[PDB]
Amino acid sequence: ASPQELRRQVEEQSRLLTAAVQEPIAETRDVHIPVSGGSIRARVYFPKKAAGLPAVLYYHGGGFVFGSIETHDHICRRLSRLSDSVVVSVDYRLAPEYKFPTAVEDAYAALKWVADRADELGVDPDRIAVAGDSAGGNLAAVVSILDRNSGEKLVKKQVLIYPVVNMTGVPTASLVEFGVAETTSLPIELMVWFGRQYLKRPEEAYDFKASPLLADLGGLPPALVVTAEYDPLRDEGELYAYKMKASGSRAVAVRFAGMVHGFVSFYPFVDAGREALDLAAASIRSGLQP
Amino acid sequence: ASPQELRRQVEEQSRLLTAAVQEPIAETRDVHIPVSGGSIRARVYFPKKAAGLPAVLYYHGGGFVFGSIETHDHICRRLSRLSDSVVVSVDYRLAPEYKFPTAVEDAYAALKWVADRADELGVDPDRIAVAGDSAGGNLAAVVSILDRNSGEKLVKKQVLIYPVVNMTGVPTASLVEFGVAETTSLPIELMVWFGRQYLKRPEEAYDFKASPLLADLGGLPPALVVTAEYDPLRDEGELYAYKMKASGSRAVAVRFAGMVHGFVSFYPFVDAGREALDLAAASIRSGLQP
Amino acid sequence: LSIAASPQELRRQVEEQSRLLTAAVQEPIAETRDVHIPVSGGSIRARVYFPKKAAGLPAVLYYHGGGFVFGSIETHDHICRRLSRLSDSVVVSVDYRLAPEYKFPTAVEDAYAALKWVADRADELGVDPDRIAVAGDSAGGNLAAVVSILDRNSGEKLVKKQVLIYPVVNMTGVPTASLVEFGVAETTSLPIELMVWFGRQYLKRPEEAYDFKASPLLADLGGLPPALVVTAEYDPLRDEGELYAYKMKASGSRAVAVRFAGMVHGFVSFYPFVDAGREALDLAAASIRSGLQP
Amino acid sequence: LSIAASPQELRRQVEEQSRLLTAAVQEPIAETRDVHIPVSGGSIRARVYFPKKAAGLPAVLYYHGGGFVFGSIETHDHICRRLSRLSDSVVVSVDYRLAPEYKFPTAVEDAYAALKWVADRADELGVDPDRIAVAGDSAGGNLAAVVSILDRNSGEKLVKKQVLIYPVVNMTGVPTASLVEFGVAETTSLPIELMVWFGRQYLKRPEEAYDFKASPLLADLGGLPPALVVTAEYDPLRDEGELYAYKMKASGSRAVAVRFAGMVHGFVSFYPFVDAGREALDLAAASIRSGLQP
């Protein structure tokens, strides 16, 4: 099936699946963010009604092809509340329609937009983080490298939840192991698919904005990377952390037992995803303390 | 060297090592708890001045031979504060002086003492947890099984931080792997030592109060077990969790990369120990919500 | 399988299942002789495999797997023939008595007795008594490891080398990471439930699990004959197998552990169909050949 | 070692170091002949090892390891003699040209050329052209794997089997879990710094790392000759080695991967001193023997 039809299914599936969670929150404001060639949508979650609050940029997962604001709305509500920070979930553009660079560029613009319109949003400028799951973690990681290179220091902390950091063809042992098994949640055939729908040409994969791990990782904001024991992205996510730390950037990698890829997403239904969001939040909260 | 001299060294070492952390807190009350054949000491940490607060029983580590209230005072202060619960650190009796049963019995009495004198302590009875690191995790696990068997339901949540759950002679692969390496923090020779100083006879090790994992683990309070990638107790700690969950008891096992045994203890100096205490707390806090 | 059923009928289903395996391969061997070995209470069968016709030949005692309840000389006849011809050794496969009928140390005792029988009957066998090794798979590896310990405690030095194929060396409830990981998997050839059942059929009193003749890993493994330990990546026994080789080495005995990728417990029996079973068998035969050089 | 020093002098320290290894063992072989093989730009040396004196013998091309910068026929003379006598094959060790002097595809080209030379000179060699295999360790395994791919793309079917000992199959910066874990360890025989340096000495333009003749793992591994892949538990190359066997299998080619416990990269070279190096060598010789049966 066509990417458009898998996208409409994953959406139906997820809403259908989260017609129950009730994640309380304070205010939610839906915004529009100017990007090259138009605008995108974002949703800001206010934990309280106050001034100078920390802010987190959440980039949803979905292989650069799926996912939406609504798709990770529950996750963002709980974060906002548990970390007590504003969360601006970004509806970055999706592939095969908008190919590689694009998603990465809006994620970056979003971030920038969030710091310049921060009085408005009632957010503290010197206290902003970037989080994301799967393809979102990637964007969160790349965005963090753009902020580094740019030298604007907008990112103070990062939370990579099962990031894909290597889009090359050089597989990992966990990649193959959990990509092939008869009980994964992230078929190797589907990952190779994501890649095709997103990258124009495939050496684009050797680019640092596509594969964040191939980049020099010195000089980056403190990072919290979460992994799943039975996730094909496990080795890479954990290797991302090692590398940051070896290059002088602070990193902590926590791996949850018995979990599969995308488990935080089923948090209202799996305990481990609860303990993981609770951690993400606590990590953000301490990371953004003045 | 004699157990007494290793005990005086570990103490000097730790205080010496934590002459800096400043863990703020609200009030601390040092108590005396009646046990069979005398009394023991405990230290209660108040996070705020209030009524009906959740409470956590912290059992310090040290192989049933070392450790003290002062030795894990920093850890207990931060917990209290981050979880916003009372923490009563228990100076259970230590081996070769007081051998196996004893430590386990005071840990249990402590727990009981804490629920009956709870109006006094200003603590909520229906909201109590048990936490502990290394030998302390063991005690926390055993105490949780005593509460189960007893049927009093005093324990609502448990936080096993690198628990030793198998004191038998049936080694684990991680046990051997990280017990022998040229860079562990938990020499296999020293563990075999702990065992000798604590157990009278060595089949005592096959007893459930010595080796919590050999027990049937159905019907236990929700548990959060934390492991270290380079810890000889890793496999057992993670196996403890699997077993609880297989027997119908809820459990989540999180393993931190690059860490060694006893790392939370060096939290003010290692980031991963920070992220781990932050998690312990968040786990306790959600676990004790009415 | 289904342990819901009796051991004897399960022994039958297994027997038919395994012989479809020996049927698929033609393994030449210069000769065979079915023998009857004296043990306490009678005799057990044994099949002697002759690689060539000569004197002073090296020999290998082979103990078949089957969880102490299944298996027979027939069940592992292909493995033994191939083993025999590649190492150029006399292989004698032992039909040790089975549980639940005959319970634990029996088999161990039959095994050790079969070893003494070979050394005593070496001239009649065309064997060089100073050149003997022991080998086996699953429960068979246990027997081989225990037999090596018995041979050591006795100070006779009959066992010059031991080849343990996916051996079970720990029969207590203290699980390993691999024990549970592959014991519980949906794709397991050695379910945890079946392993638990083997023990109930084999041991009379659950604390016999603590005897070294049942859980060899609990013994002092120093001073043992050189060991070659073969394990499988998805075998629940994997960890205890490697733990055993390490422990031996740490105690001064020589041991080498090899892990076959992509394999499950019992893959050697399927050698005709699985390339890896065949590579494993060739390593074993080469390991024996070299271990038995004068 | 110290890469702070030049390649040529490091090549010397290594040469002396490795020959203390060949010195420790006496490995009989019916015969040897040092030969000179024609390649683009001249000739490379090769040493032919004859196991016995006969016609129609099976043969194995052997490519020594050394990170494409070190090693020589002398450096692996013991391994080849032993390999030769245990498989009963003619082994021809190739002295392929080294980097940095001669850079990447050279060695690959020397290797493939050495393979064609053996098949063409088989009658003069007492070899059965239909029974040839290739083998090697570290960079030598790379050459053997690449040679197998070249032999396949050519459709000549010269390679009947390939034995890859702790092969390096990926020369890009995309690390594996094992690559970093053992590359950075204090107890590593293959530091990450040295691996990075080998690549700079071997490749002229860093994106050649993406060519299949350098990073065989990137090729379509379907339709290749049977593979036996040997890895070590603490080898940084461990994961890519096993990844390679799996990929081959998933593509329809036959492959078997064996992981030796407690070993580091290069343990086979130390076979005289390490029991496991010896067991590994015997598996390889047995794997070739069986793979080359008519």
Image (cartoon, coloured by chain):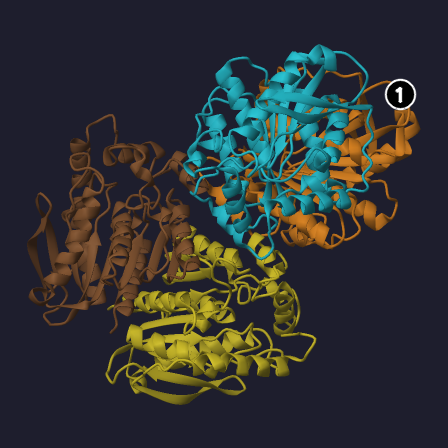
Chain colours: A cyan, B orange, C yellow, D brown
- Looking at the image, which residue is at 58% across and 28% down? A140
Question: In the figure, residue A40 lies in which quadrant?
Answer: top right
- Looking at the image, which residue is at 84% across and 33% down? B289
The answer to whether D271 appears left or right of A203 in the picture is left
Q: Quadrant of the N terminus of chain C?
A: bottom right
* Residue C48 versus residue A27 in the image, above or below: below
The single residue placed furthest to the right in the displayed view is B119
- Looking at the image, which residue is at 60% across and 45% down? A3
Q: According to the image, label 1 marks what residue?
A: B50
Query: Looking at the image, which is closer to me, B247 or A172?
Result: A172
The chain to which mark 1 is attached is B
Residue A276 appears at what percent x and percent y?
Answer: 68, 36
**Figure label count:** 1
Question: In the figure, residue D214 lies in which quadrant?
Answer: top left
* Residue C16 versus residue A159 in the image, above or below: below
Disc 1 marks a residue whose amino acid type is: Ala
- Asked which secondary structure carries label 1, the reply is loop
Can residue C249 be seen by looking at this rendering? yes
Can residue B261 be seen by looking at this rendering? no
